[PDB]
Image (cartoon, coloured by chain):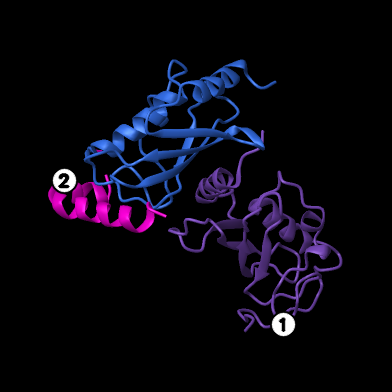
Amino acid sequence: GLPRRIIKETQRLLAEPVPGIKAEPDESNARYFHVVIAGPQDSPFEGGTFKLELFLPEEYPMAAPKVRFMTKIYHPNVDKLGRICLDILKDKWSPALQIRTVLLSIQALLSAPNPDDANDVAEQWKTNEAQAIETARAWTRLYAMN
Amino acid sequence: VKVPRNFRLLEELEEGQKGVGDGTVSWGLEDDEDMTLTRWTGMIIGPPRTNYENRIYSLKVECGPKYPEAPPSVRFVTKINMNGINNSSGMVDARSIPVLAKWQNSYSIKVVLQELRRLMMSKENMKLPQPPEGQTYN
């Protein structure tokens, strides 16, 4: 049976959305969510709209939700297949947390990136921040506007 | 539990990196930066006590936009004489391979490659004359 917790979280997402975030369940799959996060004001991603997908696996909420960026983005925490490096999506998940926490955390990651982890983009952000920010802006113009 | 394509193929990527125990089949992305997760490579070691024995077969597997609802496409790069494999293009005829002919959405790249390996084990294939080792299709 579909866990009551998933039904209630879905209702809550529809009734009280997170500002700057759209999140809707897939018509064919109640465990599958289509998410859009607006690029935060004053960040390198300002003006962009970023598509993500989220999936609630069998053992949710004991296991974390899985989340993938679908829109190409230049960010210390997002690898080349869109996988997100975020502690509460791995080690630090707990059933005390919920979908809304994950969505707010990703928005927060975009608003003010923190490059300490380890990968080429994080390294650029640490030692050549100006270029990293310009590249993130360029990719927002190129991939997050249409 | 239905796993949507974009998450299923990331699972299959991690499983392929982990590999099966004995290395008799393997799979991975053709381009490990391919966001669409569409084009994969496969590897089958020819089974023992057959005319395929010990030979390394390289394959190309395509997981289209409707995978895993729709079966993947499969092509041998290494030339192989085996029922269902076109002897000039290496393409695998889905009608000839039960796992593809009767595809179900719980199947996976691993399952397809293991099925092809089991089929090289069959009475109909195991004694088929084979081309000189190493040959490939145009």
Q: Which residue is farthest right?
A: B124
Q: According to the colouring, which chain is blue?
A: A
Chain B shade: purple
Q: Which mark is residue B13?
A: none
Q: Give the labeled residue for mark 2.
A: A126
Pointer 1: what residue?
A: B88
Same subunit, labels 1 and 2: the answer reads no
Residue A113 painted magenta: no
Q: Quadrant of residue A26?
A: top right
Magenta-tinted stretch: A117-146
Instruction: Residue at 45%, 58% (x, y): give it.
Output: B32
Q: Determine if residue A90 is in view.
A: no
Mark 1, secondary structure of its residue = loop
Q: Residue at x 26, y 52 (%)?
A: A136
Q: Amino acid at mark 1?
A: Ser
| Location of residue A101 in the rendering, given as x and y in whole percent from the top left corner | 40, 24
Mark 2 residue type:
Lys
Q: Nearer the viewer, residue B30 or B79?
A: B30
Residue B94's place in the image compared with B78, above or below, is: above
Q: Quadrant of the N terminus of chain A?
A: top right
| Chain under numbered label 2 | A
